Length: 585
Ligand SMILES: CC#C[C@H]1CN(S(=O)(=O)c2ccc(N)nc2)CCN1c1ccc([S@](=N)(=O)C(F)(F)F)cc1
Ligand SMILES: O=P(O)(O)OC[C@@H](O)[C@@H](O)[C@H](O)[C@@H](O)CO
Image 1 (cartoon, rainbow, N blue to C red):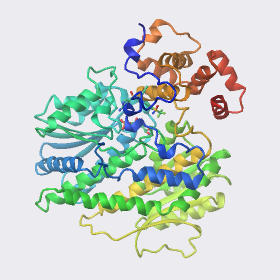
Image 2 (cartoon, helix red, strand yellow):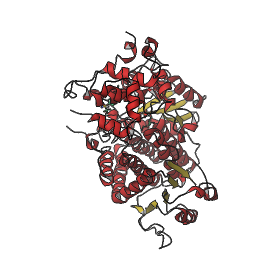
Image 3 (cartoon, helix red, strand yellow):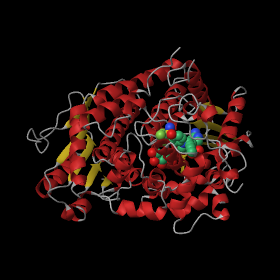
Image 4 (cartoon, helix red, strand yellow):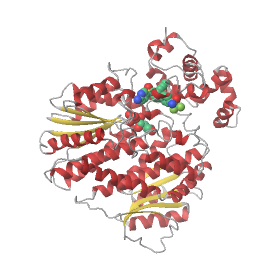
């Protein structure tokens, strides 16, 4: 029937109360799962939220139980990390002809970029040619834009890979897809397997291969799952690898920018750093060198989240500035600045928030006086500015910019990383009466730039900014239980996520939910057969331009009414959030 080709794979809605026993829940990829710790997130206060997300992030480091999924600390995963470090060594010994590519869509692509830079520095600080590069769905501009649409083409991913792999003789392709989902990566991995003599693909993500995405890619014949299963078979001969620890669901369902991007770093910085630091020691990377790093990264979570109350406050003051209708600025130096930008930009698609709502800034790259003259004029009593720096940074360039902002603002707070026994110039740096001093132990680094110190600092910031940004929006009431209902369908995964949220919250059949969704998307046109049968990219291209598509669809379902009637009902409610919330009653 028209549509069946497209919607066949979708699991039926279960009857009330049989969501577990239908086997439905056991088939939701871990990355899409609702996290039980966050079922009441929409009611938690700011301090709760910080605790719950703190807890969620902790699950990255939790160990495997006694029938269950491999995790980060499991032997199979660490053993895989060792082998892979092994393969990076082969290339590090033979840079003439060698390349290492880190690739992903969205936040996986952001993380890819950061890491490509860091390990490029490391080899430069040693006067080796850099061997690392990145790829991001939608080319380099994607790094700092919201561009959720660009991950849906395998042919794209393969092209970007063909470019950068020039006439290199040995390429290592680390494809990052938290959900084992992005068609962009799928093409890259599949290409590599078709040319083993040059390419070595390493797939990274956080679902078991049996939960890997399995719907058809529009421009490609194989699914992510087949690709991944085939890589796993090649692992027995050491010509492909799959690194896929479970780290548990996101605190905000399907928000893989969070735990997923963090685990992406934890996992890859660990493994590559190991490979580097053990080559010039003339010694294979072992689990013991990796574990050192993982435990460091695990200390870092505890270090970070012990500043919880102060974190909870910054959230409260980001919430307020947006609750009024102010803006929030995230101002940071070197790499921490970048990560500030990345968090801000992600708030656009993740929350439907405007690019001014939470904006990042590096000294987007608007330098000292340029910030003084450009952005400074437009500050306001009710805004919030956030400063993010180490003590190694240049605190003159910092004190000046804060000195200025104090006048036009007063809601300033800061994020200062420091070795122990570094002191904060101006004992009246108050200015900041209640800093977020994150003071690090002294660790035993040997490479010139102290790269482990860097990775700690990045991760810790990411955790803070993510927890803050996400938290602030929850407090505003924009999140439903632990789901972002009112997302903008801008790729096929978000289309599927929308459909799943309609089944979840309404309890109504696969076919009704699909119908209401497609009606909501294409209104005022009605369901033709062409539309039913149309590929998911056609729905996406039309929905991406609309507002409240999902809430309208859900309302049509709950009231069993037309799109005309549910739109009218929406417009006559005080807000989207109350309309939906009380239709659920
Ligand atoms: C329809 C449907 C569905 C699934 C799978 N889609 S997906 O894009 O096809 C996908 C994405 C990743 C992956 N590994 N496999 C499949 C992504 C969204 N997804 C999903 C999301 C949430 C839920 S959920 N547990 O019902 C709740 F929304 F409440 F979390 C269930 C399924
Ligand atoms: O790494 P994945 O599963 O392939 O997802 C890639 C991107 O869709 C994803 O990073 C998304 O942009 C983020 O908003 C998730 O919160």
